[PDB]
Amino acid sequence: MVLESTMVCVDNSEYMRNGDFLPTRLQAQQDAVNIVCHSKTRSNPENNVGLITLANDCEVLTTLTPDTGRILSKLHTVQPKGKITFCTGIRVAHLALKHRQGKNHKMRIIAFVGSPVEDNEKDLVKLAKRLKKEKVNVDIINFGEEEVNTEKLTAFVNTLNGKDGTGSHLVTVPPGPSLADALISSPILAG
Amino acid sequence: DIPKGYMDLMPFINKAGCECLNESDEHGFDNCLRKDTTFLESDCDEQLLITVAFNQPVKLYSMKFQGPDNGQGPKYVKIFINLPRSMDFEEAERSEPTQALELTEDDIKEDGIVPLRYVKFQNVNSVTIFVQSNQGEEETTRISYFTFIGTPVQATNMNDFKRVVGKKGESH
Amino acid sequence: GGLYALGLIHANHGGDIIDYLLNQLKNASNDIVRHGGSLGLGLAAMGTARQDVYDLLKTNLYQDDAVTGEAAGLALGLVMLGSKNAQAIEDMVGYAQETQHEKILRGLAVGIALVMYGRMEEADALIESLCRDKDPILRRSGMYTVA
Amino acid sequence: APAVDTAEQVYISSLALLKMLKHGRAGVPMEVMGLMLGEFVDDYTVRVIDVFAMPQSGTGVSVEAVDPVFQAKMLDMLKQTGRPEMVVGWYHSHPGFGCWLSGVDINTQQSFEALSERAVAVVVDPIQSVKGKVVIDAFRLINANMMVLGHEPRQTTSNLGHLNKPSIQALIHGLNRHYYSITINYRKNELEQKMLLNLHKKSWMEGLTLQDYSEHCKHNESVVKEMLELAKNYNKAVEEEDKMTPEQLAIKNVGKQDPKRHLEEHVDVLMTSNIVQCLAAMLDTVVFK
Amino acid sequence: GILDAGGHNVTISLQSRTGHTHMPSVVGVLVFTQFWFWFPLSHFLSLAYTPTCVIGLNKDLKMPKVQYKSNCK
Amino acid sequence: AVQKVVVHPLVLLSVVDHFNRIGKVGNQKRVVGVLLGSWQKKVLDVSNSFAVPFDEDDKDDSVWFLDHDYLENMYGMFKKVNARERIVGWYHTGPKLHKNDIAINELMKRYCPNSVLVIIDVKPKDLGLPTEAYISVEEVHDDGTPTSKTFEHVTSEIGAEEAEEVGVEHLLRDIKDTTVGTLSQRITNQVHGLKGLNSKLLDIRSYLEKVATGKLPINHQIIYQLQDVFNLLPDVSLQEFVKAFYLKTNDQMVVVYLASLIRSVVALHNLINNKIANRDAEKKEG
Ligand SMILES: [Zn+2]
């Protein structure tokens, strides 16, 4: 019911292609977004979710839309053939978020971190600092091979909203056989 | 108080459009829109950006940017008009304001009304106030009461339209 | 009309009538009555340069009510007649290239015209600054300011 | 009783006129229509900034043609780009018919007026407005209940007869009887004229190109031959100098002929062409090595 | 109205009696010329009507029935 | 390849409007939009355009947003209004290209493969031609140099279809110059040409200075083309041409002389006719 626009950032880098998760990472993201996108619209029928690919560039494949069909359909042919750039991904997701057609929805972002992020620790925190000022809650969930609970990533979520913040979770998924059930249990119903 | 022939735009404020940035969870935006002691505070810094949206194009005469006398009341207010997209803090300082206002202590009092240049605000559809400091230089600023006084501009709502005279299926 | 009519009788010589006119202009429907009011007050204190009258005339002008402007502008000019008031000329023009309501300019065109009455060299800048402005109404005000 | 003072103007931006003329010629055989976006800045001025075409439909130019879904969505999308204007009126072409409103048009205008008492309606004949002239009269229904009072209910003003006089090809289709015209004035401003001046602007290269001498010599030879024959008449016309009321001779032989009009008129052409050509020739000799 | 303004007893002359520029009179015409843009401004020509008169005031308030003559040839 | 991109007057008058719409409140750099138009043999006709919400950041020069749905939906409406327009490229009024142009151009390549970006310098009003048209080419640079995206240049020219032409001609109607030219305007056409040729030659000099001082890369191509222009000079000092120039200069002076004489005899005849006129009326008055 909480009016919020979920700008889901789905990874499509090359490492996203090795299936430490049973069938493949992508289906995990592709299955995962299926629930997060569906989770938000079910919670509130006035909601809207868009997706930003994060590898090799920051494409905006589907702008912020309520209809979940477009997000699901666009997921296909996501073609994981790039290198993740999370430094810019959040900005473009937020900058696109700033174009919210309705100005009332709260802000909530879901990032699909599935590759090793090569970002200076100082840069990530400064990005987090800009998010704090502008009151956007972003959830980070990690997939596939990556320095488990990257220190750069973990510092990001903590400064994301601390001092008794909303708790934009850095939900770390158990690598190995696991569906979005971990991604749906904790983050999807509570972010 | 209010001037002759002008009415507060509280009824005209679009709850959907309005959104604050840096608003603290405990004291939110809705608090400063009520004529109560309930107020709004900025969580992450003294800078705050409180935007509002009006149902139909309104005109602006005098806003009452009241603030607590503890020193956390607003000090420097930058107003923008009809912003196509929400504003960014970094880009908000850069851009030139429609009317750069230096609040004085007399204004922040409960009875203080700050006059705006009526000429510049003639077709405002959404106004964004940017509090750049509080009087006491406190960690968080506060807006006790904040609303706009003007007149409503009659807007042609084409959504209604609807034929009023004539018969359907008639050509030139 | 009557309030404007009253000014004509006490034209150039209001004396006491100005104080009544000031009070009456303030209490008005913010319509035609304000239009006649400013013209009457401006006519009554024509050249008085009185600050009290000038401040009220400005507020009506800043009201920006179109019909109100066309009279407040002239009333603004007449009260400042031949005063070369640097604030008035800067203020009067500043409204010109900042306001819609062509009508308000039409008063301001003559309104800033009379503010330079008879200096004959003293400004010669409004004459040149105005004549270059793109807004045709201000140009006319520049040409009148030559007159 | 409010009144549309004749001084009231419908300001048409430089954008709108090109876009309104473009739409009209787009479907010139048929009739096109669209809503105009503007502001009612005050009683005496109806300012129109942008116009957006409402898609041609079989109904024609009528209330039904106004697709509420198309207009509600288009407005919504133009609000994001930075044009939060209000629907200030509607326009429709009139393939050569003129600048008048038919019965069906009147019913439309009455509808638009229902939402705001100042919704101006324009025309825009793309066939007549074919040269420097632009035939686009604005119109606002004069409510029929004001027959007791004065039609065109204007007041103190004096720009009623200016910028136009009641056009006959329209006064017959109902003017000052059910629809009155509103003075149309275009809000062209600098930074818009300058960009339009580029339409036919030449370039740096032009003005230094020396023409071509083969057709220049032919042209110089051609005109000098033609002027020669015109001198023969000049000799005959002057050497005649017949004095049988010469002032009447100078008025019974006026047909744009020998004496001067076909005379130095050519001298100006002949001398302008050579001087410019020569000056171009010498400038190039200096600039280019 | 202009021809018979004031009952044939006033005249418009921006120049003052002693060669000065009559500020009330000159202002009157300028704002009057701005009647093309506003009819109610028309009355401002009232300022330009200076009674073409000579009063035989001898004392402060005395208004003697002075009998004086002109030169209509 | 596109030989020309003829920009119609309406587009540069909507872009100007588009720049004013935003810059008036949201002070920002280039305003990006979509450019519609009909194709031709090779000359792309730009007949209309519309704005697309575009926000950018000076940091990382790749945190931007060009809305997709707004671009898709807008064109969904316009193809309804007029069906001869297809999306053909984009426009931005920032006079100098950005680092974001290549990436965004790749996007507009998703709607029209032969996408041409037209830079409209809305703010400047100068020598002329406020449109600069660019394409996207990815070549191996034949001459053994790294590959990259780059924007190739396409000749731009501003024209007008009949309908807009009528509107434009009236729209000026106060500063248009006489088409005849006359001696006054023809000469000004040359002081104008001289000013340009100097101005173009001065842009060339600064760049040559830049390559001379190293601050810029020796193109190795187009660099010697400027050497081509440097050999195409006339060499007027040649005797055989020097004779042939005096002949044509002399060939023309004898026509301006005959033109001058005719205008003089007509002048005297007009004074004699006039001297008779006032004199005859002078005597006839008595
Ligand atoms: Zn019709």
Image (tube, coloured by chain):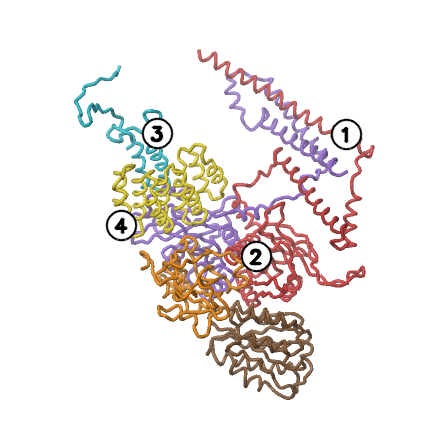
- The chain letter under disc 1 is F
Figure colour of chain C: yellow
The answer to whether tags 3 and 1 share a subunit is no
The cyan one among the chains is E
The answer to whether tags 4 and 2 share a subunit is no
Report the Cα–Cα distance between label 1 and label 2: 52 Å
Instruction: Answer whether residue F10 is visible to the viewer in this image.
Output: yes
Q: Which residue is mark 4?
A: D148
Give me the disc on residue E14. 3
Report the Cα–Cα distance between label 4 and label 2: 48 Å
Taking depth in this image into account, of F14 and E41 the one nearest to the observer is: E41
Q: Are marks 1 and 2 in contact (CB under 8 Å)?
A: no
The red one among the chains is F
Circle 3 packing at 10 Å, graded few (<14), some (14-19), many (20+), is many
Q: Is residue F185 left or right of residue D104?
A: right
Question: Depth-wise, is mark 3 or mark 1 nearer the camera?
Answer: 3
